[PDB]
Amino acid sequence: AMGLPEEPSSPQESTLKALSLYEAHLSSYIMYLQTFLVKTKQKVNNKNYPEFTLFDTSKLKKDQTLKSIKTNIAALKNHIDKIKPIAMQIYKKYSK
Figure 1 (cartoon, one colour):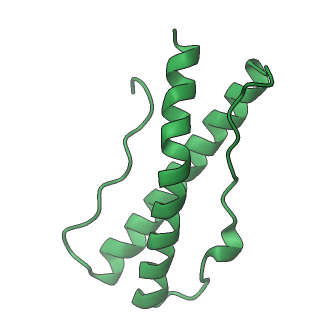
Figure 2 (cartoon, rainbow, N blue to C red; figure 1 turned 60 degrees about the horizontal axis):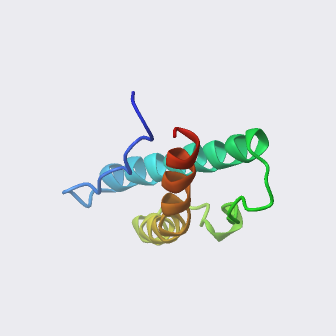
Figure 3 (tube, helix red, strand yellow; figure 1 turned 90 degrees about the vertical axis):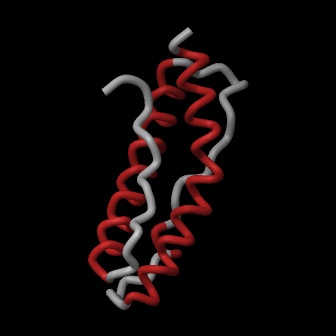
């Protein structure tokens, strides 16, 4: 792999298993980006380092219903919209 991984693609199919797997990839992609941001702060720690929020897993529904899975997917996508642009800028700044 070169560079940051790409955001997981939405499934064509809205089956419980397509959406459950999509939810798992999105959670995993967030933890990749957050880890990358935390590790890169540690190495280059000038006060300028941009601020980010860590994902609050208490916003995730713990039941396994196609409705609560769809709601989790929305919450993870909203979080990615916050941190992806920051992760991509920190990657470029420090791969310079």
